[PDB]
Image: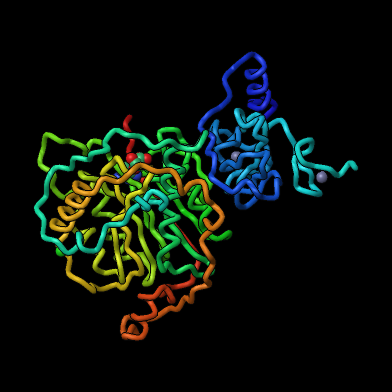
Length: 116
Length: 300
Ligand SMILES: Nc1ncnc2c1ncn2[C@@H]1O[C@H](CO)[C@@H](O)[C@H]1O
Ligand SMILES: [Cl-]
Ligand SMILES: [Zn+2]
Ligand SMILES: [Zn+2]
């Protein structure tokens, strides 16, 4: 398939053009005293984050399209994703645009302190 | 009252013992809305309070626990209730959910279709249903016991709920079934639980705690629903979101409850006593296999 829809680029371009972020991401009630890691088996928001059900924050899940992983696996479905409170207006955009540190499990740039 | 700091209110036992006639439900606080924490959906708040209440019962919580959740989709295309159940349940709990309409879910597996199409090889430790048809809320017509998905739920419980297991099935003034109330008498204990965030509604969760597979009590479900409505009609419940703000003890404790496979002849009074205390589950510990029947038609 030389042709494949690039949903990620479409959403980024849509946001940059002033489009409204995807809504109805499922925010969880929690203590907000968790580890702050990015993607966890139960909500782990710290005081600076909100925790969301993972599937509802996944662009591919929400758009009903194939995941880019060759086996179609989803990093978020069945887990909880922690989103900085300052970015919680657009959890899908946040998870799409950012990366988890493979070492400490925090978001690169939003918790990871490994370059230190 | 002090009820406002609870997750909700369970039917007081004395109301269960009445012989009321069925009346229209007229709630004092109807149309009031609770103030939910910023950005929190009603269905997350509601399931959170339900789970907070279930934490107070003698649920069996085995290793390799199996839970099935009917009516899990929303008009939003997501599954907020499933997200709360998976937060509540021990990590690794097998969670299956289902709905008539398509939705995306955090459950381990999701089946889309009428619940009547759903079959499972295995038994379950907990059954949750939020299935509801708002077309039942017809105040101009008689309020009779409903069939439809309630007929499926009654059979599903009797065929596929492990002994010792529990259920929470959503009902309303008009969405109810007499046999389902009668089946509550096949559990060691039961109630009708109203969440404090949705106390302005005639909704409740009918909860059966520790299934015994046989009647412990003979319940007339037409009378029991009348008793439930009488309770709601005479006991205004203050809308409250207070319990949502303390999540420290929310997770369901992994009790490691024992699972045994037993044939009906071996279920003696001792076994029945263990089942009744939340200390035993009886079912196979095989693989979890589910399916949905699909009707095939060629329209050409
Ligand atoms: N017979 C049914 N089978 C499956 N889901 C149902 C059924 N009736 C209602 N629901 C679901 O119950 C939820 C509550 O209205 C809705 O998501 C609706 O699709
Ligand atoms: Cl009765
Ligand atoms: Zn996904
Ligand atoms: Zn790191």
